[PDB]
Image 1 (cartoon, rainbow over the protein chains, first blue to last red):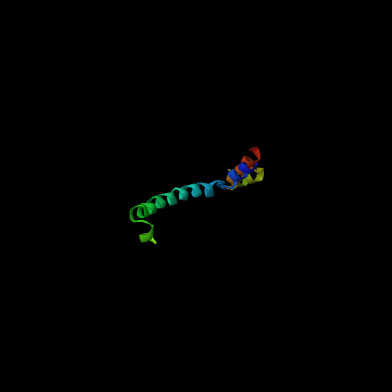
Image 2: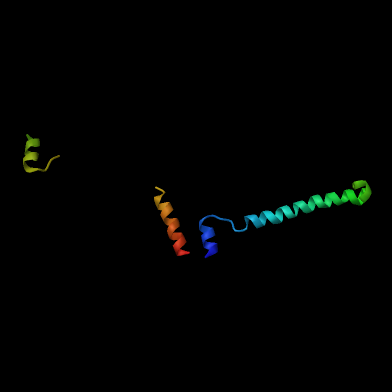
Length: 47
Length: 29
């Protein structure tokens, strides 16, 4: 019954969850760029 | 004179349903 009311009201039940997993791989990209700095330069220089 | 004769005798010469179908679409589901 929950899916057919969300179908009626045009409510996406996973719009928050699809945007959650799409920013979680987007913040994994900048993390993959951020540790390229610390692997290259080191922890004392970065601090 | 025909007019009088004819007279004498009396023989003269939207979306509401689009809203409705989506209501039955809910109840059919």
